Length: 330
Image 1 (tube, rainbow, N blue to C red):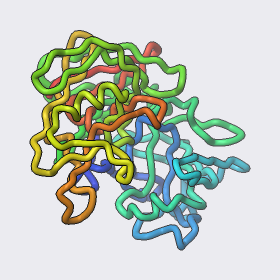
Image 2 (image 1 turned 60 degrees about the vertical axis):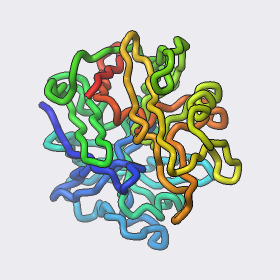
Image 3 (image 1 turned 45 degrees about the horizontal axis):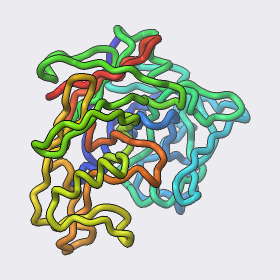
């Protein structure tokens, strides 16, 4: 079996992408953020503190004839400012673009951090990292992909994110009409539970390619591209007037500047990020300072190939017994 679903940017800056997901019987459709950097499927629900719900569509387990409370199970996922989202766990039927899984753990949020409350267009997250990161206690639960693996024609899913445009998540097959050239596959380390791989280097604009190993994770749930300080400094040095701002928290640049492209290596292949993809607009309404899409990972502790990088490619998440990542130009 296979599944295919359209994913849509939530705003004009491609800050995040939402994908419709059917939960329960009869179906309740929620718009979830597909996140290859986490492993929990959690949703706003009828159990969420009413003051923390601001326009989201909520999952109501009492109206689903297939929902079952998972007795005594809880979940808790931690975030930046010490905030956390947490709640209890149901099992229910979950379908993505025609692909149906029964008995999927659906984590119902009892409380969510303010950042999720402020974002009325995201009804929850669907984690697609490896199941060892799932936070359900005392019994860890499997991801949607892990539960679907057996019935898929091929144990893969692909991410084809659009630039200011809709895109596609496919499960169980590789659409050979969605990319050009060849898919280059590279080894994945699962030791930390992420889709972790090693880029072979980078180039800024039309400059020389620098061969250097950059270990990082493919994370559809992160907007920007976070790279080592040396790489990020070399990029912004080519943008006249760009500087690192502590008040803003990263590199900013004059909105009138034209940004150079950024190339990253996948084996012997090269993926080029057009400069327009790195522009994330004015830091505040009316400002002539614009926020950069490539930022330093020094404070994060891990390099993250987020949406900025992934939307420049067709990306294969190969969940075979030896997992790999595939990149193709498109």
